Image: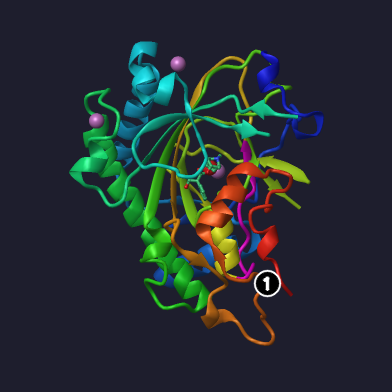
Amino acid sequence: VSESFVAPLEKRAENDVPLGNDVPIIDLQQDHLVVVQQITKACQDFGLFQVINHGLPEKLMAETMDVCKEFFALPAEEKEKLQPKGEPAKFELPLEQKAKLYVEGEQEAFLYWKDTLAHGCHPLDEELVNSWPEKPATYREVVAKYSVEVRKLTMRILDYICEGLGLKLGYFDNELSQIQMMLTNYYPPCPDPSSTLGSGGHYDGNLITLLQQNLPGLQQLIEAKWIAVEPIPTAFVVNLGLTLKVITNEKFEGSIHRVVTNPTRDRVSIATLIGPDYSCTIEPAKELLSQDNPPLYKPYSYAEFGEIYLSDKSDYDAGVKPYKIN
Ligand SMILES: CN1[C@@H]2CC[C@H]1C[C@@H](OC(=O)[C@H](CO)c1ccccc1)C2
Ligand SMILES: [O]
Ligand SMILES: [Sr+2]
Ligand SMILES: [Sr+2]
Ligand SMILES: [V+3]
């Protein structure tokens, strides 16, 4: 493997990470109060859970995975059309909503063993969709339907979260969820998995993420122990973001997770990252604060947070360290 992709010794994954048997799998077709209670407990104790019987069509999930895999099978000459000035874009502000191919890593500088297609999905209009990939031919039709369905499911989950916290329904149905970035991640086979990472350990910086996977590689950090997240092809993995950790005043955990490489087979995952506009002010929900529950963060600019989150990887929560109080 090229030295560009060699992770620092301490960040390298061990070869036998055990299955996370305690990862909650929440059936959304249970009684309403049972769903609210199970989601609440998962958010409080884990910050990562799976949802099943979630009302998003299984056929649409399969068609979206198909067209995402078809995109990454396109030849070089087509993929160049999504590389600004001949190279992949970087996860840095301003983060534009038009489709680009992205490179990612840490600055002992190294790169993640990953190609990422990213674009905005909300609101859907002619201008946004016309900035999506031209190939495959059905990408725009399928991903337009997928993005609406994934948003619908995310807003259902956020309203379950509202009921669990004692916030009014629709608390997050505003500026706090106005950005919907869809990241299609391609992990080609890696000749030295012991030295590389598909994706470094991170919180998602946004509010909430729904992740679709059909192959192993996703791992979560629990009380410095890593566990493997079982791939369920018809489920969504829910990762609570650093923004939700702040707004709930740490009553909810954020999901710290990474992706390991595979020597023999490729892997495609689809992450829908919903969260605030860059103009937003983030603070602990006033409605939940008291003398017994004082705010642990001061108000901050999401744009200012974003710049630190995307550059400083000295700690998982480096993004919010400057805003910590009490
Ligand atoms: C694995 N990496 C992590 C998470 C996804 C991917 C790319 C990057 O995250 C983002 O670019 C998101 C886009 O919403 C972001 C940007 C600024 C603020 C909050 C969130 C870091
Ligand atoms: O992510
Ligand atoms: Sr190029
Ligand atoms: Sr175009
Ligand atoms: V993530």
Residue 30 visible in this rendered orientation of the protein: no
- Image quadrant where residue 276 sits: bottom left
For disc 1, the marked residue is: 296
61 shown above or below 32? above
Q: Residue at x 68, y 34 (%)?
A: 107
Position of the N terminus by quadrant: top right
Q: Front-most of 38 and 73?
A: 73
238 shown above or below 175? above
Q: Residue at x 47, y 25 (%)?
A: 88
Q: Could you tell me the amino acid type at mark 1?
A: Leu
- In this view, which residue lies farthest toward the left? 126
- In this view, which residue lies farthest toward the right? 9
> Is residue 250 inside the magenta stretch?
yes
- Residue span colored magenta: 249-258
Taking the image as shown, residue 97 lies to the left or right of residue 113, namely left
Give the percent coordinates (x, y) of residue 145.
25, 43
40 shown above or below 203? below
Give the percent coordinates (x, y) of residue 73.
38, 16
